[PDB]
Length: 162
Ligand SMILES: [Cl-]
Ligand SMILES: [Cl-]
Image (cartoon, rainbow, N blue to C red; front, side, top):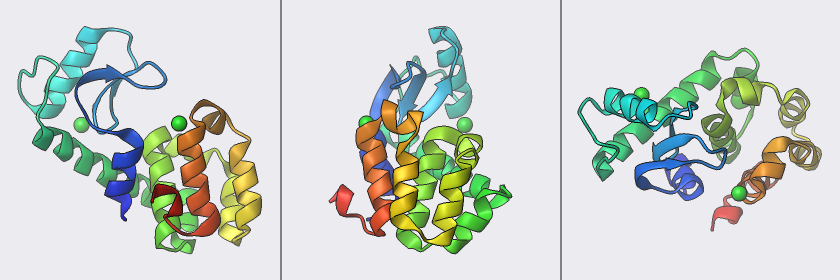
């Protein structure tokens, strides 16, 4: 298992513009287009991202390309963040993937806000961090996904995804 396969499972793949769990226009593999309520604004961002007049529909290759860029950006966001970097550096491979997943989902800013959880991860207090990670809107809004990511932090294995 790896970061790509993990996120492909959590986000799924959709070739036409759709609304995410929060109701925002998205496409492909969890690629947020805009938070704006307008479909046109969404279509405009899509075309700008792909480089062609899409009409709200992309190909698989196009979805994957956005996905590669998005994963790359998540990692780079973590490494550039003063709060996140040190955590990330302290973790093993599986747990690093869990942190990337969260950043992909909520943004660096969002994750950087889990101050207490981050400290616990850094200290390697797995069970404690898992409980703390669960006391959040994130867990309450997308519990199944949250549960899978939390298990990875807790156990250091991909069991939840197998
Ligand atoms: Cl983009
Ligand atoms: Cl969920």
